[PDB]
Amino acid sequence: LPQSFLLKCLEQMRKVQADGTALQETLCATHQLCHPEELVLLGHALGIPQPPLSSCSSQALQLMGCLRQLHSGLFLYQGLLQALAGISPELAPTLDTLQLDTTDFAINIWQQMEDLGMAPTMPAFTSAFQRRAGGVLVASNLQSFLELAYRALRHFA
C-alpha cells in the first residue's frame, strides 16, 4: 500500500483509540463500568455484533479481503455509535468526536479500495444503563479491532 496511506491510517486509528479511551475512562470513574471483560455476556444479551477480521489474520491474509472486512466492520461500528445516541449529555460530546473520527477513517479505507479497484441489524439500547455498558463494550471492541487491522496493513508492506 503507499506509505502515505499507512501513515494516514496510523494517525487516524490512534485518534479513534484516544477517543475510545476517553469514553472508557469517564464511564468507569462515573459509573464503575471499568472491566469490559465482565460485560461480555451482557453485550451478547444486547446483540452487540463483533466484526470479523478473518482475512486480516495470517492464515487467511488477502489484501482485498482484509480491506473489505476492515471497512464493513468500521461501517458497522458507525451504526453502533449512532445507536448509543450520545449515551448521556455528559458523554455525548466524547461520542460525537469518536463518531467523527471513525467516519474519517472509514472514508479513507474506502477511498483506498477505490484507488485499487477493489471496492466495495442494529442493537436497541433503551435504558441508560444499556447505553452506558454498550458504550464501554463498543469502545473496547473498536480498539482491539483497529490494533488488528493495523498489524495486518503494516505487513502489506
Image (tube, rainbow, N blue to C red):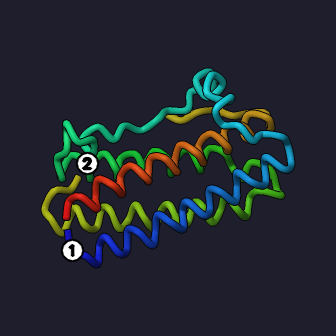
- Expressed as whole percent of the image width and height from the top left, the position of residue 54 reads 29, 37
Disc 1 residue type (three-letter): Pro
- Answer with the quarter of the image where residue 115 lies: bottom left
Residue sitting at the far right: 30
The residue at the point 79 percent across, 35 percent down is: 129
- Expressed as whole percent of the image width and height from the top left, the position of residue 100 reads 55, 66
Residue sitting at the far left: 117
Badge 1 element: loop
Horizontal placement of 124 versus 126: left or right?
Answer: left
In which quadrant will I find the C terminus?
bottom left
The residue at the point 70 percent across, 55 percent down is: 23
Residue 3's place in the image compared with 60, above or below, is below
- Expressed as whole percent of the image width and height from the top left, the position of residue 132 reads 75, 41
Q: Residues within 10 Å of mark 1 (few under 14, many from 20)?
A: few
Q: Which mark is residue 87?
A: none
Horizontal placement of 14 versus 94: left or right?
Answer: left
Residue that numbered label 2 is attached to: 66
In which quadrant will I find the N terminus?
bottom left
Residue 128's place in the image compared with 16, above or below, is above
Q: Earlier in the sequence, mark 2 or mark 1?
A: 1
The residue at the point 19 percent across, 36 percent down is: 59
Q: Which mark is residue 2?
A: 1
**C-alpha distance separating marks 2 and 1:** 16 Å
119 and 58: which is toward the camera:
58
30 and 132: which is toward the camera:
30
Disc 2 residue type (three-letter): Cys
The residue at the point 79 percent across, 46 percent down is: 28
Horizontal placement of 93 versus 46: left or right?
Answer: right
Badge 2 element: helix
